[PDB]
Image (cartoon, helix red, strand yellow):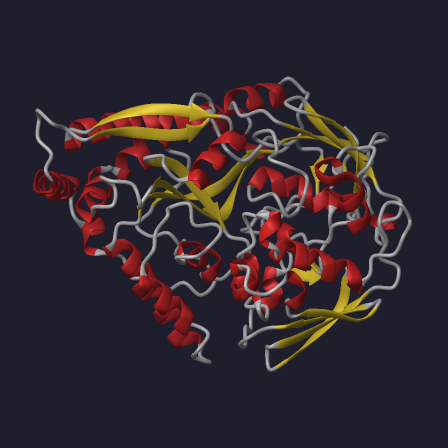
Length: 517
């Protein structure tokens, strides 16, 4: 943290953050969500990290070079260490990226290496080549070299993500799935794991072996697993919680803006809220059905009547304010809702649905006040506008993600947040073979458009290709875009260091501090 001249620090430097749900895991190779990544940035540090405004900055690598954007050389700081005092080396990164690529690890983020195009990744994922053929090598203990199959000018931006953080081979090998328990875990971020009580709390304590430990101010941070946004706000206003999770409740928000304006932080956020359709499951494998659901959802009502928290109605998957996004707003989004409803009704009538044999399906969402209220509203809107019946089903976060990967569900509530600020951080998830493709969407035309983006050496042609890829997604009604999120949360007046300037919201507790109050 960089404490401004003149601020008086509190005697006790402890922080309590709500984290939205119980994490799936603390293993960087087994996680995919926001809550997981929140804890992951405090414990495991990769080659680069985000600074307080979100700019990619030195992490374990102090400096780096590239040759033709295809060979990237990272110079690792000599004093980078794990919490047991041992050095973090380039061998740790070789092992870790191999483990991430290895199909036996079954990481949800195995395709992150395809997104960066590390050499030989496709064959490794397919089981055609061993993970040791991955295009990474340690040239020495402090030098990590990555070789890609084609120029990727934004490659370094991907490196702040948890999936490419290092993991300690000896703990993984000796303890297997229990390597992340407090007694066994070894970490290289600013914090160490002190306590992990499932569905109660995660408590982290400062890691004195961290190379930048002298700048760390918070000594202990607790992450809570509260999925009820109302309860989160309640425990924040009671004094227990210092920073809520950034999912806000419909019951109280309007009230909060009026009652505590200075504590309500609302900043840009590169995330899209949408209803994920299982594209491989009839009758959702019919574009007419999917298009009807997309058109009959009334975004004006959701965004301004039922939620009204500053979200913008969405018509795409990639947020239009992503760096590099120049999207074409489709004609259906400018229509009146009445016109969208008649088109939807006509497609559904064309697909075979009648009043006597209506379309009935499930709407899966993870436990949440917000998601429940929004799914009840969406069910009502679809019932009134299109005559479809939906059966709401809630699941806890970890189960919910498992269900979507299992891919036999019908429609699921969904939200994707950028991992790096560039449209492929969204678009690569819809590639036929992506490990993150829970839409189960497979379009050869879409895949080709994205493949073509690194075959041009021009940002203008790349942007035009991303716009066409979004148009192809839209044409196929792969998803139901609802709204672009805003990062809205409460932060006590005494919490310093949270700028809200990073649109990816990659917070590091090592950057925060408690002001005397």
